[PDB]
Image (cartoon, coloured by chain):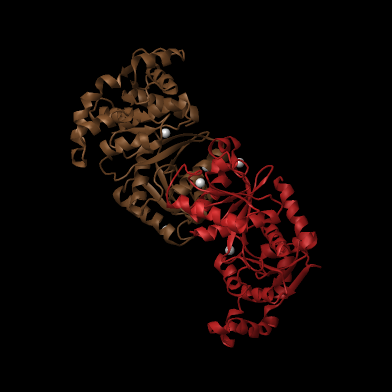
Chain colours: A red, B brown
Amino acid sequence: LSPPAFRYQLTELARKAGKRIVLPEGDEPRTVKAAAICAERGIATCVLLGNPAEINRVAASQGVELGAGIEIVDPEVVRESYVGRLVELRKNKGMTETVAREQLEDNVVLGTLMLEQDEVDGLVSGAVHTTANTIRPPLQLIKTAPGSSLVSSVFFMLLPEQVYVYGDCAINPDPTAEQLAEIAIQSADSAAAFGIEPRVAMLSYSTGTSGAGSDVEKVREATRLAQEKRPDLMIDGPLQYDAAVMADVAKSKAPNSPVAGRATVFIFPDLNTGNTTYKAVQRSADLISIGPMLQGMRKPVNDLSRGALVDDIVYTIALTAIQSAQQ
Amino acid sequence: LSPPAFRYQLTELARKAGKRIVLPEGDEPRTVKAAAICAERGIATCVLLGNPAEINRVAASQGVELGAGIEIVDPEVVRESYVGRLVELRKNKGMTETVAREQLEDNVVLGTLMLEQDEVDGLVSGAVHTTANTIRPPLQLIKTAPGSSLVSSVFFMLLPEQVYVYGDCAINPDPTAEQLAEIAIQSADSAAAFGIEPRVAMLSYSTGTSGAGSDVEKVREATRLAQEKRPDLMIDGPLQYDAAVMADVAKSKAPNSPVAGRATVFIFPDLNTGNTTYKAVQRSADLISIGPMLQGMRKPVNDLSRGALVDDIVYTIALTAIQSAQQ
Ligand SMILES: [Cl-]
Ligand SMILES: [Cl-]
Ligand SMILES: [K+]
Ligand SMILES: [K+]
Ligand code: NA
Ligand code: NA
């Protein structure tokens, strides 16, 4: 699975999904250009939230036509029709009609209510907003998937001939043992859904009992808890990074391990570890990453980097559509 | 500073130091062969602790002569002469003459007492023993250097044209803010002593205020505390790894930073982060590392990997001799 091969696999899987993805940042130039690519290539039907005139002016300003597969929704027209639904959804938290109308001025809230009404299949935003702005309404309204008590994330690491899965390198600062086992299971399910055989390495500064301490025991607990809920999955830990990827190190420090030496899914003990290793490997191996992709949400939601490129948005919409077919 | 250039710089600095390094594993084949190289190249005078006949048989078994610069000490001859000193050193902890004699059967204890008696300048062991076996007697008897409340460690990361310093990637599992500031200062002093201009990046999953949480505040506290004790040092944090090494990321996320974009010393928030990133970078960039090197000890002590090679031992003796001239 080379980087071009994996990127095409995302295109193939998204086409077979045949999903509708709402884009709250409907008039954003990068998002308009990416939506037209997804429609022309069959990656997804893109629902743009914004003024039809402005979106078409932005589309014309970038040499892009919005034909089939592009559906523009004017928030001013449809906003009031979702007020009653939002009041009903948050009535026990003190939602009023006036407050609900105030919240619906944000296109992410509007797209989330469209997502909750099963009018679209997924939501992508964040090119010109914060991560919290993208995920807070879905967290409040869509909630977590059954069997998940939290949302985590993964990065797809595109090596020259294979794809690794890293997580959680963006969201959860300090997972407990129970949460870490949940992150490992979510990440392995994500890997399998995107064509990656999950061999899950629970990372630590200790390989087995080479090191001791509360930090090592948390990874050991999470390993056992994850194996309890999913006896079918190949999980092992604790493992240092070299033991997870090198067969020679595996044969010397963890020879009875079904994961060591050939791990494909790498679960980091905390965000310090995950984000630092993710950033360092991106520079040192000079490889390519796709993500981060959220996991554990009841319906797919994903947040873009504020400096994302058009192609970054294109494949993020693909991931979101593929996640919709997974559920 | 290419890897060959840096390795020669260690040779030059060790020669100028002109130190004596005691080797408790005196009859170990790899250690005997490395000691003769250090003596012939002028890296250090090596004091081998073992049976003179056995050491010479091991030396002859590897095509190696032990001439000038090699001094063999028979533990059976000199052990009793250090019993009274050990009793005096640990009298308040319940040391007796019989217990002291029992402890002196371990050559590391004997070499540590030689180190404490200023008969040698540094100690290297661990090729056939655990790390705890190497460092416990010095920790009990030599103690920490003035201004240091703990011992930490660094790895020298030999990039194609420069050398980075990583720490602490081996010893301290979860440093407090005060300890982390101490690790940063020790690591910068180590870097400068080995010909590396210290620009210290205090690593985190947050660049500045990009992320919040107790983990980020610890790095922020350690950054300020380290700057308080050493106003002359270039320290900054918190910084993600990409902000520390990439000028473009630095100009966008930390433009007022005197370290971001050109860091040479990388201080990891905990052992999970340090060891995982160290192991991952070694595989991803396929670079070369030297270490780990202890720091903060009153007199230099260093521990070998049990799978170390002869050349690994050679340059570890060099590091230890260089550390002796630093103090
Ligand atoms: Cl274990
Ligand atoms: Cl800050
Ligand atoms: K964002
Ligand atoms: K050792
Ligand atoms: Na690898
Ligand atoms: Na670099």
- Residue at position x 40%, y 36% in the image: B131
Tell me if I can see residue A169 in this picture: no
Residue lying at the far bottom of the rendered structure = A97
| Image x and y of residue A215, in percent | 45, 52
| Residue located at (32% from left, 17% from top) | B71
Seen as rendered, the residue at the extreme front is B98
Residue B73, image x, y percentages:
30, 19
Q: In the image, is residue B77 above or below residue A258?
A: above
User: Where A229 sits versus B23, above or below?
Assistant: below
Foreground: B10 or A322? A322
Q: Is A203 in front, or is B253?
A: A203
* Drawn side of residue B149 relative to residue B248, left or right: left
Residue A321's image quarter? bottom right
> What residue is shown at x 62% (from left), y 62% (from top)?
A295
Where's residue B156, x and y in %? 45, 36
Task: Residue A36: tell me if it is visible.
Answer: yes
Place residue A107 in its image quadrant. bottom right
As displayed, is residue B275 above or below residue A187?
above
Is residue A37 depicted above or below B189 in this figure?
A: below
Residue A114 position in % (x across, y down): 69, 75
Q: Quadrant of the C terminus of chain B?
A: top left
